[PDB]
Image (tube, rainbow, N blue to C red):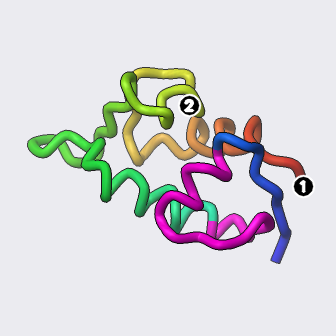
Amino acid sequence: ETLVRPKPLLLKLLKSVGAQKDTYTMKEVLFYLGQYIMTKRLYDEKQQHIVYCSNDLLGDLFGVPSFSVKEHRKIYTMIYRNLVV
């Protein structure tokens, strides 16, 4: 699998939920980002596809105050800005 090296902020968030490494697969990046969002309950309780992140560090990764998990283009584009191949 293609390996990626998260930039400092992305790396910090992934490590905050138990990832121990500096190099990741895209599956692992998504796994730990998902766990990050879950464990900080950034999603809307009543509209659970929607993540509200304007006061979280996640909001600085995305550069938006919220997003839907359905928005794969936005999500992958954010991830692209925050790693090196």
Residue located beneath label 1 in the image: 85
Whole-angstrom CA distance, mark 1 to mark 2, is: 19 Å
Residue 82 located within the stretch drawn in magenta: no
Range of the magenta residues? 10-28
Image check: 77 left or right of 48?
A: right
Residue 26, numbered circle: none
Report the residue at 40% width, 22% height from top.
65
Rendered location of residue 6, percent (x, y): 75, 52
Rendered location of residue 53, percent (x, y): 38, 31
Rendered location of residue 21, percent (x, y): 72, 71
Above or below for 72 versus 19: above
Above or below for 6 versus 50: below
Label 2: few (<14), some (14–19) or many (≥20) C-alpha neighbours in 10 Å:
many
Residue 20 located within the stretch drawn in magenta: yes
Report the residue at 58% width, 35% height from top.
74
Quadrant hosting residue 55: top left
Name the amino acid, label 2. Phe
Residue 27 or residue 38, whichever sits in front? 38
Image check: 12 left or right of 37?
A: right
Residue located beneath label 2 in the image: 62
Image check: 79 left or right of 18?
A: right
* Disc nearer the start of the sequence (1/2): 2
**CB within 8 Å, label 1 to label 2:** no
The secondary structure type at the circle numbered 1 is loop
Report the residue at 32% width, 32% height from top.
52
